[PDB]
Image (spheres, coloured by chain):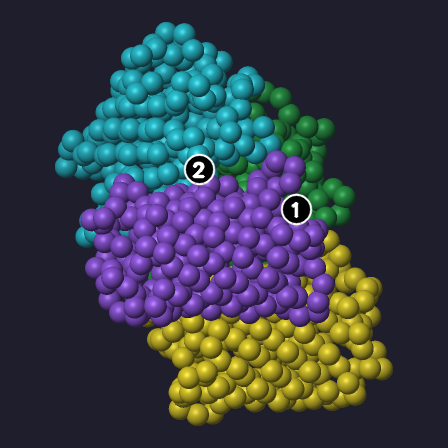
Chain colours: A green, B cyan, C purple, D yellow
């Protein structure tokens, strides 16, 4: 895909609401699509000012499968989708009753990916790890990719690691949709590593890095 | 509660996104809080103009427990919450993988309830009853109300009725939060009846009526 | 149904396994089918002798919808099923990860119902309310009955009450199957009250009483 | 572990019930614990004689993590558990409402593993892929292993492949328990490949082969 280059840039805008707390997020990043790597910086602004009111890890995976190392031969559902574009829809089902839904659209112009997202979380326990900001990051995961009714689906039982060492389970279910039809891949898996680093005391300024590789299974 | 009168008015504003379709909804209604009844009219405006793109029934229950007939003696968690206000958070888990989260805030001034909500739905099958607008309304339900960690929770296995007569299951889980502490009720049940009537071909203009009664169990 | 009389007797046999603990249960009871009431006594024998190793409340609802007061006119799916017989299948999804599946068969001879069941529970936390025997009984419930693919289904979000006053959620999903076709009822609800009383220190000897009424909704 | 040799034998006995159909299974196999491979042959006998009444794939994963290639250094939770023994508990949550629970115990004598299991399935749609025997086998999976409350847990979103090419989702949740404490492993993943081959028309005689490797993640 001549449209996707070796080095790309990214810009992000998110509108969200978590447990009734409204916020917006702005971000910028750079990545190497073929290498499967990317790093970006974000700034969260709570509607009522103030420090980030919940764990940023619930938002991290919302902030682009084009950044996945695929074997050259294998149909790359994500890279093939550009320049037309793609949309994503993800359900996050947490083990303690919190649930979040997120949907986003990605467009491309030149070397720049514009990512516009909406995030909504509800029912997180007021003293749980999300609202109390007790998480440290996601454990490395293996997301199963399958085709269903013409679109690619991703499923993974993810684990958010906690400050003292324990874990908190979250089932992810995602629909990856292309604007135009592309050659479909066979079922496969995407291995991920994502790291979150707070840049300020409040957690409002944060950096994220993801490494992802696709494996023929 | 002198603040809640025999006849009240309502005004609504919703910002939402379903399967990537953005929309806003405006509405107005009237109700009898002590009788447990209310009727309102809504207008949905799709971001891209055009007929309503999905079943309005997924939004109906988002558009106020003050409209519940409670036995005079029983603590009325909802009526007691005013004038301070209340917030609601609901998870809708559909049997076909669609999930929606909704959160809203209700405030009161005089005889007027202002209801401001956010709705987000994802993963609904493109040919399922929601996206294909094949539903007719919710079957009468019995929502169990229980207290958990200081707030009232509502749980119900709801069924959306379909055009040909079949049913489509949806589990509802809701947190009912008050701005200030109120006397808590014992576990109980709220029986509901809700009717949706389209006023235009597109389904963009719709009327809703709900009847609800609380039963000591 | 001349086959179902005003006063009936019951006999029970259960083979089960919970968290690897094998056990069998024997029981006897009496009830008034038209009144919707019944009381029975059980004896649990653990494969390894010893006191009952888990909360009997997980088994209680397994130990007959013929004991439901139905309005004379309404199709009684359960009473109509005899003398041919019925089979039941129930999934219990607990909020802490424990899950139990149960299936049973009921036959009738004269005034006697023979109930033969199988129960299997797994993944209950070793220190949770089930394994630590911290429950007191089920809160009164409203089970929604719907027809799906030719059989009657029952759905309810049940709550097991705990020793200190809290609650523990369990979603029940049941298929009610008849040996021969019967006239189907419209969707409705069955209201229940079930009480468990230990007769010995170990909880191995226990009495259960259920009251159930069907409501046209 | 001197107790686990390069070549081992296996014998199996299962008592089960699926949608009210009782059956028993007997089996024998051979495997290479360190290589992560094993092959066994089974014979299912339905209580009422007759061909196997449901997809054998729901039982396959019930029929031993000692057969996993682990890097020599990494704590092998499963091999360390012998000679004392281990017990397993697994919840299978199918996307169409069917649910199965299974629990089993494995003991060792000499080169022989004895595996005794109980299987119970309910609520599978009468015309679904399980009851209609429309499955072909499990897609290759990546099971996440995490430690929780002192025992190892396995989680995976598995997919059962169907005769025409489609897929059927099943979430697996398993507790792996040792009879005595062992050194715990860090969170990791087990990659699996399992193949089922019918040896008779009815599917009552079947062979299974599994290859599994643990990856440090």
For the N terminus of chain C, the quadrant is: bottom left
Picture coordinates of residue A113 (x, y %)? 48, 44
Residue D146 or C151: which is nearer the viewer? C151
Identified at 64% across, 78% down, the residue is D116
Residue B28 shows in this picture: no
Which image quadrant is residue B27 in?
A: top left
Please tell me the numbered disc located at residue A22: none
List the residue tagged with mark 2: B144
Residue at the spot 25% in from the left edge and 46% down from the top edge: C71
Q: Residue farthest to the right?
A: D2
**Whether labels 1 and 2 share one chain:** no
Name the residue: 72% across, 57% down: D147
At label 1, counting other C-alpha atoms closer than 10 Å, the crowd grade (few under 14, some 14-19, many 20 or more) is: some
**Which chain is disc 1 placed on?**
C
For residue D23, side relative to residue A83 (left or right): right
Which dot marks residue C134?
1
Report if the CB atoms under discs 1 and 2 are less than 8 Å apart.
no
Which residue is at a point 65% across and 37% down the rendered structure image?
A: C164
Where residue A10 appears, as percent x and y from the top left, is 53, 42
Where is residue B37? Give x, y as percent.
28, 23
Q: Nearer the viewer, residue C38 or B35?
A: C38
Q: For mark 2, does the 10 Å Cα neighbourhood hold few (<14), some (14 to 19), or many (20 or more) residues?
A: many
User: For the residues marked 1 and 2, what is the alpha-carbon distance in whole angstroms?
Assistant: 22 Å
Q: Position of residue A214 (x, y in %)?
A: 56, 64
Looking at the image, residue B96 lies above or below residue B176: below
Chain letter of disc 2 in the image: B
Q: Is residue C185 left or right of residue A105?
A: left
Q: Secondary structure at mark 2?
A: strand
Looking at the picture, tell me which residue is in the foreground, A22 or C178: C178
| Left or right: where A79 falls relative to B181 | left
Q: Quadrant of the C terminus of chain C?
A: top left
Label 1: state its secondary structure.
Answer: loop
């Amino acid at each position: 895909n001549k449209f996707i280059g070796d080095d790309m840039k990214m810009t992000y805008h998110m509108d969200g609401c978590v447990n009734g707390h409204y916020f917006t997020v702005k971000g910028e990043g750079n990545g190497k699509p073929y290498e499967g790597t990317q790093t970006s910086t974000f700034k969260v602004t709570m509607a009522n000012g103030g420090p980030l009111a919940f764990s940023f890890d619930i938002l991290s995976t919302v902030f682009n499968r084009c950044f996945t190392a695929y074997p050259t031969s294998m149909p790359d559902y994500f890279k093939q989708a550009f320049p037309d574009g793609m949309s994503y829809e993800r359900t996050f089902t947490y083990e303690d009753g919190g649930v979040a839904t997120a949907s986003w659209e990605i467009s491309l112009k030149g070397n720049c990916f514009e990512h516009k997202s909406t995030f909504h979380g509800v029912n997180f326990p007021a003293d749980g790890p999300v609202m109390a900001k007790k998480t440290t990051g996601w454990d490395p995961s293996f997301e199963k990719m399958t085709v269903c009714d013409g679109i690619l689906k991703g499923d993974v039982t993810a684990f958010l690691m906690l400050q003292g060492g324990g874990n908190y389970r979250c089932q992810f279910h995602t629909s990856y949709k292309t604007k135009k039809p592309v050659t479909m891949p066979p079922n496969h898996v995407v291995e991920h590593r994502i790291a979150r680093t707070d840049l300020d005391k409040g957690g409002n300024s944060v950096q994220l890095t993801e490494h992802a590789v696709a494996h023929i299974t």
